Length: 182
Image (cartoon, rainbow, N blue to C red; front, top):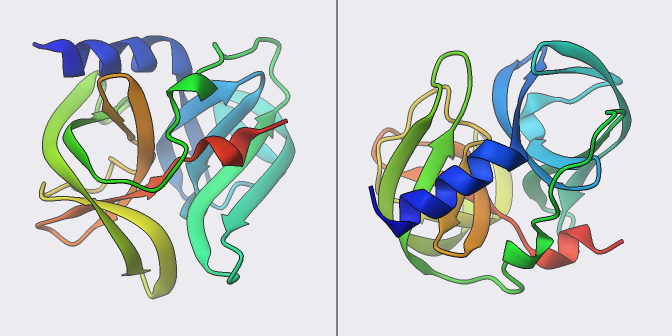
């Protein structure tokens, strides 16, 4: 409808796949080469389904900060025959607040879904399903089951992936450029 949705659509059309684990179906953001991200509570194993095709996982790393606190981001390298468009230049370098964000989801339950969530706060610490978690972004939108792994964007930046909500607020794990240096 506007330039926020235009940026979000450009990311969804080229840089997302549908990932299925034993824990459900998730929006999965491809970042560069065969490297993608998913919420850690997806419990990625040796094998994952990518757009309903059996795919070997070459590597999976559940990120934690230097105090050994959960960040809720798992970085997966997929045994796929094709690379993602490199979008690392759209990742923020530092923790920050944002205006006018969009949350975009693409699954069997929620195809081509886009939500204008508005203002995004650097919330920081969250007890997420009982797990102390850092680098959480918060938006005042009543997000629901089916949205985990959804991409949070502003115009020109990919800032996070949706990992939970409390019925009134939604919560994303930050994406930082430093997670994806090679």
